[PDB]
Amino acid sequence: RPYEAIWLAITDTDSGYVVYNYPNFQDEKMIAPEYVAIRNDSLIYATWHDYPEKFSLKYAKIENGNNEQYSFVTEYHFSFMWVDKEKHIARWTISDIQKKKTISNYLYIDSRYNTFPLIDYQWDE
Amino acid sequence: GVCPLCGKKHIDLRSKIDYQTQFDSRFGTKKEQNVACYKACKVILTNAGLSPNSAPNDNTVIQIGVESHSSSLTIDFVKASEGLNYINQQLETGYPILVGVDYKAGSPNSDKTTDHFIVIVGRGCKNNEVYYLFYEVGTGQQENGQYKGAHENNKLYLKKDNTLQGTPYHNSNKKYIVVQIRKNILSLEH
Ligand SMILES: [Ca+2]
Image (tube, rainbow over all chains, first blue to last red; front, side, top):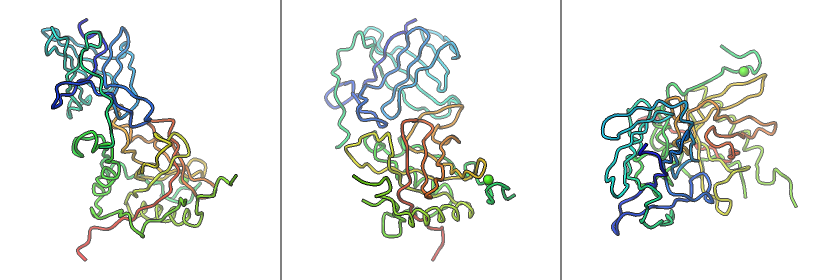
């Protein structure tokens, strides 16, 4: 289970990759990076614009492809694939369940190996 | 037909008016999406066949909310009835309405007055208790293959003082009251 970790979304910037830390659109006191976290029976999908969604994997459709690729369907379609396994960097391609529109396809760092800075995102440009 | 209980037709325009979330790369980067609530509501108005010049922030709006006290100090009740009437007559013509909401509860930042809008797209009743359906552009969550902001539990309830108050399906903490009605402009040459 290579996908089993807290995956923090990274953003490429002019000064290198960072983990942005967002005050949530629903509640400015809730401040967190975006992430996908898989620990046992749970898949947590957390964006900057909504409360985190914690899905029970016992109701999910889970498939494994080749080369340690995996997909999970709850209310969204999540596909995991390594990007740089030595740097513990993976990509989560997140789509609607019809697979018609891609929602995001960020790179992520396993939080246990994260060396990028956590930078508090500043909404008021 | 007309409803026995409430005496009006029940209306649900959702199948004719596509939903739009504000959390969409068509509005730009995250910082632009963050302030795109009005723009997404305007996409919904043009999805319904109205002019892109609809819902200006000018003196045609119906301004219901005005700036030890009563609970109704900031509500103009005559304007509340006017806004209600305009909503009923647009829905009966087949058009949605873009409205501004304030928070009874669950503001994302009580220290600020960030403008928020929703779009009313329907009307019904339960035992003569009138409700209005709305599209909430302020969510990107999806469920059962659709956006949560298009779900039928996005309902405003008509209160005894003719204000409209309710809760979006994606965030049970938010309690809206409708404080501003913006005007539709038809697609006409002159
Ligand atoms: Ca009725």
